Length: 118
Length: 104
Length: 146
Length: 90
Ligand SMILES: Cc1ncsc1-c1ccc(CNC(=O)[C@@H]2C[C@@H](O)CN2C(=O)[C@@H](NC(=O)C2(F)CC2)C(C)(C)C)c(OCCc2ccc(CN3CCN(c4cc(-c5ccccc5O)nnc4N)CC3)cc2)c1
Image 1 (cartoon, chains in turn yellow, orange, cyan, blue):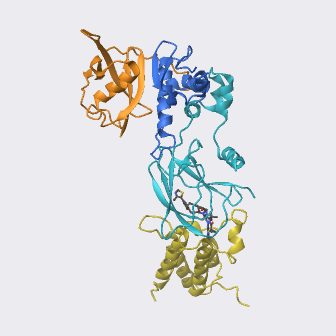
Image 2 (tube, each protein chain N blue to C red; image 1 turned 60 degrees about the horizontal axis):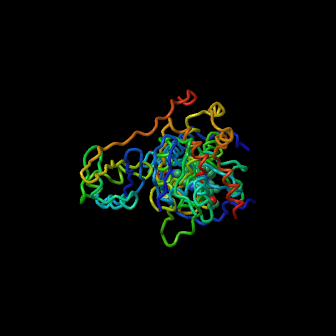
Image 3 (spheres, chains in turn orange, blue, brown, cyan; image 1 turned 90 degrees about the horizontal axis):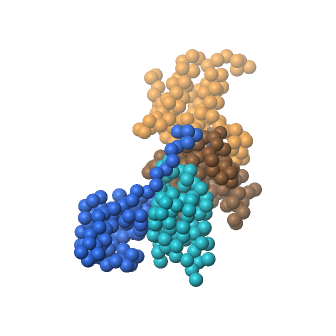
């Protein structure tokens, strides 16, 4: 029950480098692939998303759980970013730009993470 | 390629259409059907320059570009009666009133 | 559940929106509840491959005046399911407006609605200028047709 | 085949019958054995000529597979054209 203590500053500095690379990423057309994923629609805007998508999460919440040390390792962070991307993929299905954007944001995450200078 | 003309004489204006490869003589046949005057009895103009039997409307400048259904091109018409040649005369349309200040 | 609505059929369908008109086109997607959703505009002559879904209603207006436009010569657009790997083409064109409607459009574009009634025209035309084109009025007429 | 349309200042506009029948008012005036000429003592030259241009534009681009262009109306004739259109029902 020492779950109060924060993550070591080097770990928080690492997570924020990865999630900033993902969110700031632009394709060769200068388009910010992550913008649609920053914040989820409201249940009244899009109830069909919450009917189907069952564990909802956006980058707003992901980068929140970094501030408050909910993720205890880089793997805990990857589990949500993959869940975010898979949520978008199962709701919109292949053939949609949002699907294919989340394919790429998955790739950027693993490139950004595989940059460990350690 | 359809071209859309506005054949004008004095205070008569004929609305008709032809093809860009249609001939000036072929307008004169269309005008003969409407005004009952054979091709020899009529002279077609495009801004003071006499038009030419045997020439296509495209070669006279009438294209899909310049003679559009919503903005037809003008062809001047003058008649010949035996030895008499009237001058080409096209009376102007009426002028519009000045804009109400509501718009301007 | 309105009669003019999109069906929540999770069946993807590629569609090519092509604005072949001189207007700035506002595509309007009809909700699953038949509610109009405005989508990003298209400059004149512009086209874009668009991902949509089978059984979804689409509608197209002038983005500035909400004048009604045509899609494949009809007012409504529904994508079929794509046959093999072939996008469905949506040709967006002007309609042949009545002479009266086109005049109303131009007078509406020059006279601000405050001065509609300052124009010295038959008073049955004041109310014609005030009947601005919008999506709900078209949905009402297009619905009652079926 | 061709019908005559006179303005208030005497200009004669000869158009196809199927073109002039675009107007509902003109359709009633015509064939109401059948009529070939119509006179309008309250529509000027610069309005009918533009009215007749709309007839050409309607018949050509109605049910067309082409790219439909905008019908142009200069500001100085919009009002007169509006009641001309309202009167002719077209
Ligand atoms: C370029 C261009 N030029 C002129 S028009 C145009 C253009 C055309 C199309 C699109 C995108 N395509 C669509 O929206 C198609 C069209 C129609 O069939 C309906 N539809 C759908 O996806 C529906 N989905 C479905 O029916 C299903 F998926 C169930 C099958 C819907 C609207 C999501 C209910 C576009 O896109 C740019 C404009 C545009 C369009 C819509 C929106 C608002 N959205 C709504 C919700 N959305 C989503 C967020 C997340 C999500 C969010 C945060 C975190 C994790 C997440 O998984 N996941 N899924 C979403 N659909 C965010 C923004 C914003 C911008 C631009």
